[PDB]
Amino acid sequence: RVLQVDIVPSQGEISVGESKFFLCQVAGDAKDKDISWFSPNGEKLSPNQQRISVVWNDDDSSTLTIYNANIDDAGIYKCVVTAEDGTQSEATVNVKIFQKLMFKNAPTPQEFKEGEDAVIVCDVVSSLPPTIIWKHKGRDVILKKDVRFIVLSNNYLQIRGIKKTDEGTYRCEGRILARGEINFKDIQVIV
Amino acid sequence: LQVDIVPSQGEISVGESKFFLCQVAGDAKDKDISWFSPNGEKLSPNQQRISVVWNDDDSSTLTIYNANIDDAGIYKCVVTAEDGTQSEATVNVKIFQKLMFKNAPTPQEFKEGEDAVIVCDVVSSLPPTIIWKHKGRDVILKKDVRFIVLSNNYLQIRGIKKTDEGTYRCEGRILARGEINFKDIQVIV
């Protein structure tokens, strides 16, 4: 039997905060061997830790479990098996981390300096580029036809010289065109 | 006439939202665009949970917010043109429940000598396999007939002893997808 190693699933994509495991399966002799996992940085992973878990199942398999995934867990992980005579073989598995459209920081209420230049904060995270739309009472602010309203490149909404009749509920809406994903956060703007 | 829906098919996670754009190869032509739910109901423009929004002469958008299992099914976009003839497109909407725990009370207390039932309610669109652990070790390794995993995944410990106290893990896995989730439950005797 020519020493061989495989990982199942052969690849994976874990959503932020969720968990997945990968089995390193060996096909070699019928003896004892060493199966070691290495993280993307090329460093060996210690077994039995609670979040980035490496558990020994039997002589021919070790399981890697990435619990409560975060974007920094992304990368090519490697499993290397060393038979008793020193012979080695390895397999790699590319792990991607996916961040669905979410609002990292969209405070409410958001109070403002009357007559001052307001900037409504809306920090969005998403692996896929989102298209942002700001609404007031469910209507795209761009339709107000007011030069004072400008959507900034960081998705924040600027309202120059804000007035009281500008107060109300502003929704920061994110969509992923052609894929159908949408999420929003309603923000109470107070003047 | 031609009718198209994008995304062509969609899977919405329970509690999340997804939108579907119905587009007609529009032109200088009058025509009506309407959305119908899986049960055949005509969905009218609204800004409610099952939203329908008129975009322009050639398109209307259906948005399903805070999706629940009863929203599953084939939705239909029909385009009736000038006389009363029609064309359609359909989109199959799946509601996806990821491997999660509806209930996993902690701690859970039982009286020594009593038959204890440790509560763990797991939900998942895809049927998972359950493993119960005590101190991080699979309970079957005890080879103790007092430990029985019930049909609903609850862990029963007959005549629970003080020595059975500790951290139990109700772990669910979906091998086919390499998915896993768990909840630790403190058992007090």
Image (spheres, coloured by chain):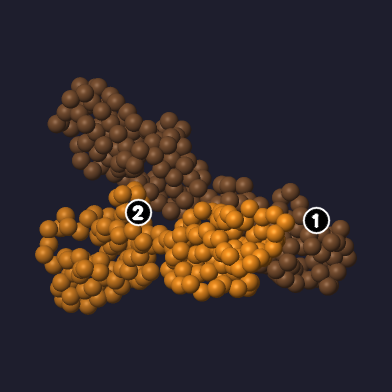
Chain colours: A brown, B orange
Answer yes or no: is residue B174 visible: yes
Identify residue type, mark 2. Ile
Q: Which mark is residue A150?
A: 1
- The residue that disc 2 covers is B180
Q: Quadrant of residue B156?
A: bottom left
Give the residue at x 29% y 37%: A24
Instruction: Please identify the quadrant where the N terminus of chain A is shown.
Output: top left
Q: Chain of mark 2?
A: B
Q: Position of residue A62 (x, y in %)?
A: 27, 40
Does residue B47 appear left or right of residue B102 in this picture?
A: right
Q: Position of residue B173 (x, y in %)?
A: 31, 54
Does residue B169 appear left or right of residue A137 in this picture?
A: left
Identify residue type, mark 1. Ile
Q: Chain of mark 1?
A: A
**Depicted A186 relative to depicted A24: above or below:** below
Instruction: Give the class, few, some or many, for how many residues have Cα within 10 Å of label 1's Cα (few <14, many ≥20).
Output: some
Q: Secondary structure at mark 2?
A: strand
Give the residue at x 54% y 61%: B88
**Depicted A51 relative to depicted B15: above or below:** above
Give the residue at x 44% y 66%: B72
Q: Looking at this view, is B92 or A98 the one in front?
A: B92
Give the residue at x 43% y 30%: A42
Q: Label 1 near label 2: C-beta < 8 Å? A: no
Answer yes or no: is residue B62 visible: no
Instruction: Report the Cα–Cα distance between label 2 and label 1.
Output: 44 Å
Q: Quadrant of residue B19?
A: bottom right
Instruction: Please identify the quadrant where the C terminus of chain A is shown.
Output: bottom right
